[PDB]
Image (cartoon, rainbow, N blue to C red; front, side, top):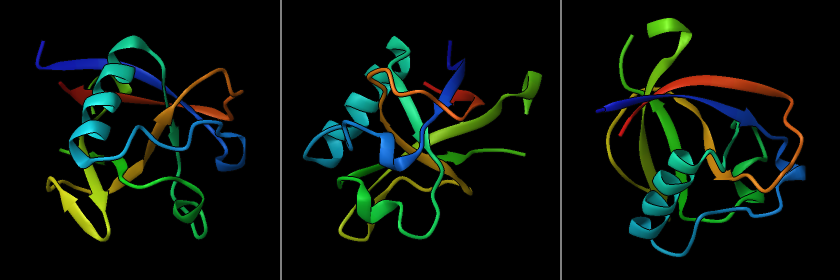
Length: 113
């Protein structure tokens, strides 16, 4: 399927144990996609002071369209030293590995895979 319905656990930035997916734009997009498939991906909502507490490169989910079955259609965009790889809509948050942190909420997305 070109799209997959996921429910992503929303984590508080200070709870996150593994603060990024790796060391290159290509690796973080690769790892983010693998963790999304394996159900081991969390979402941190971006506000003042969040991104400096996480590791670059960043992987964002961004709104790809204006929401089947409650699921917002999203795609992945990476960012390293102020350059983004991908072009999409509004940021829903930054992806991180989920290693058992307790979420505050769930974000239903339809991921362009």
